Length: 261
Ligand SMILES: CC[C@@H](Oc1cccc(CN(CCCOc2ccc(OC)cc2)c2nc3ccccc3o2)c1)C(=O)O
Ligand SMILES: CCCCCCCCO[C@@H]1O[C@H](CO)[C@@H](O)[C@H](O)[C@H]1O
Image 1 (cartoon, rainbow, N blue to C red):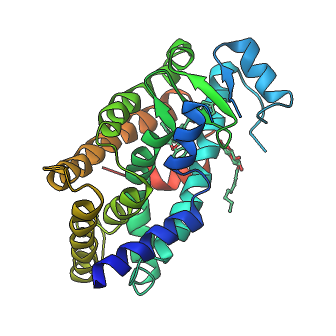
Image 2 (cartoon, rainbow, N blue to C red):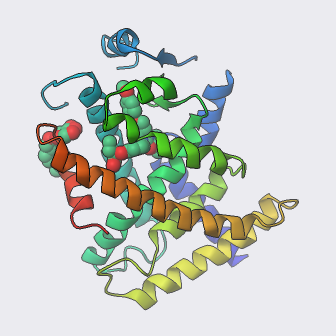
């Protein structure tokens, strides 16, 4: 009862704050308008010249994709921040504790939600109006071609669990409310909120996925998988900042990756 309403509150905060939902994504990816496919240089250009679509000064094809990728991340961080403010008691934390949770949590949540817009062949872009192929991303020059590929591997496995948006709302909330983030001041308070979230998640999963047996423990493992995925992503990003000294890294991403792990 308490948990059912708590889950509903989180769900509505999710629907309120995220422009792209899995319901919308799967509808686009299954055909019910069709996205413009971006599979090489020429189609990427066509996607820029109206159709589908501010950025740093143009450098090259691979850096351009890198820049558009960052812009989308920054926008999703804005959404996750507003979503977190609706998680009961998150706003009661001191401001720097809120930032600490978002700093170490947003990319874990981003990569979880990324699975919603992905299939084995590519992912939606531009609010679902475009589709960039996995192959085209593989064809970019290193190191940029190695950024997104490992996320496809996680996403395909994650999509096998067949979560819906109501499940994901609680899942993302549990990711953000994480008591072991470095520098967190009020660990007991954050652990207490997370426990409420996780209890609501188990209650919600058995009501929404009755025939799903080990779904809750599987999602706990997914949370651990996302932390290592992000650790390896932070390494790549920290490397690229050192290697690609002429490519711009958005200030928000610089701050997120600042001595992270
Ligand atoms: C770069 C540094 C960046 O790493 C990454 C690595 C992998 C994935 C992301 C986040 N992401 C980008 C998808 C593709 O992004 C494009 C965009 C345009 C394009 O070609 C024109 C090709 C790829 C995303 N979208 C979402 C939509 C809904 C929900 C969650 C979403 O998560 C960031 C970081 O560290 O933040
Ligand atoms: C309060 C606003 C936060 C941004 C402050 C400075 C923004 C500097 O410029 C940023 O560089 C990024 C590099 O990819 C671009 O992608 C961004 O679109 C651009 O705004």
